[PDB]
Image (tube, rainbow, N blue to C red; front, side, top):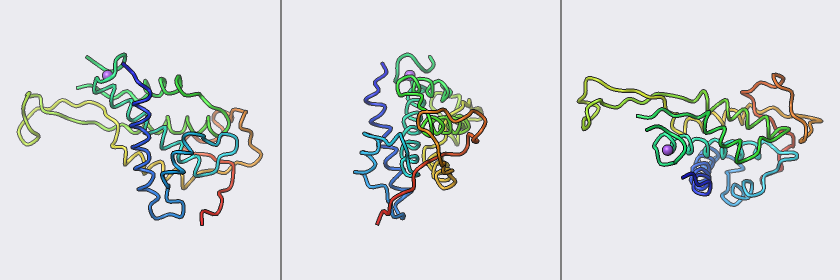
Length: 194
Ligand code: NA
């Protein structure tokens, strides 16, 4: 049975580790205190570039966790009966629980959504019940999400290439097919983290 408390918990832990690893050298080195506070009370009116990353990496980690756990059959209501990952299904349960959003927030959730949809790889396992990879001559493959570290690198890149918006509203939907879906957006300048 789906528990959003456990999913979010595991997601945010994974998200924090990726955040602290990707920013360990930067001036804003993703301190745990600020990361958690950004998730407990996210800036939704005029987010800066770091607000955007934290929300993005957190959403991505939660969906990655939900997608993976569903395929592993640990969550009732989703999964199989080798089970292929279904990130789109997970993205829908995410948009149900958490809001759809608007302004920069809404657009960025779509950006993260599209990324996870194109973050599929495949994993193969031996047909034999107890065979290792160096043994079997026949394997069965299913679609699975990339390791989260790779998705995290993509988000870091999108964080680097983010577009700043001027005169944008947090209550208006950014026009569909106006801003590319592979670009994150932010509105506010970042403060001096030193
Ligand atoms: Na499941």
